[PDB]
Length: 128
Length: 128
Image: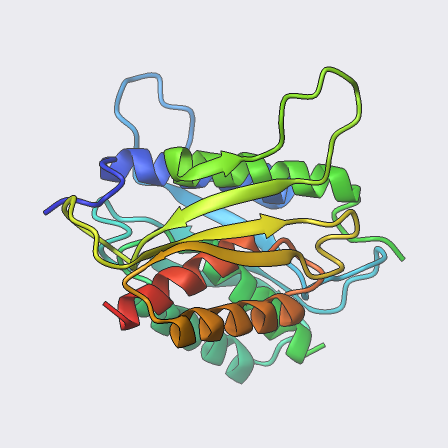
């Protein structure tokens, strides 16, 4: 009745955060403060995302992907927010948020932030 | 004229392998032998993939995702192969391979093995 990997929800979430930091690096940020105790707060991360395959150093379209993973993630959808949108209209931001929440529902059962991030990168490329 | 991350192709490929090992763990395998010299062969990995959100311990449909990344990856598509297919017909395996190579073409410019792996997991769930 448990996931085939045999890992708990915190281990699956912690492994995804390590994977996100390895690929995105400085564009990834764990917004949780350094806890002096043994309790780990639910992960809240920020991903600065650019159009797919962006080159150079001059950006025109970008947005920050704010993801808060509840304890039952990824068996439940995470809290998705879009911040610091640049070069996007209000209708395009609402559309992207609706598509991400729709993607998150179909992605339940597996960690999904990598798929949400690529969906944003592909979306930004279509509006660039 | 270079990627916005400022990282080279080997660094982007090595970061993806570290991310893949963190999430998939034992289902991920680097098929490159341990080189005693300083030259790193092109990454050739194997991903044992199951239907999305598979529970229990009894598997019915599964396949291994064989990916070989050329030096210019991800600016060029990687070599994709499907091995050890279980519960899938020959037509379904050829379809999955065609969809993965189509996905890889649209994903050029960013690392894509995570998107290829989820596409397989979602595909296996539709044939389960």
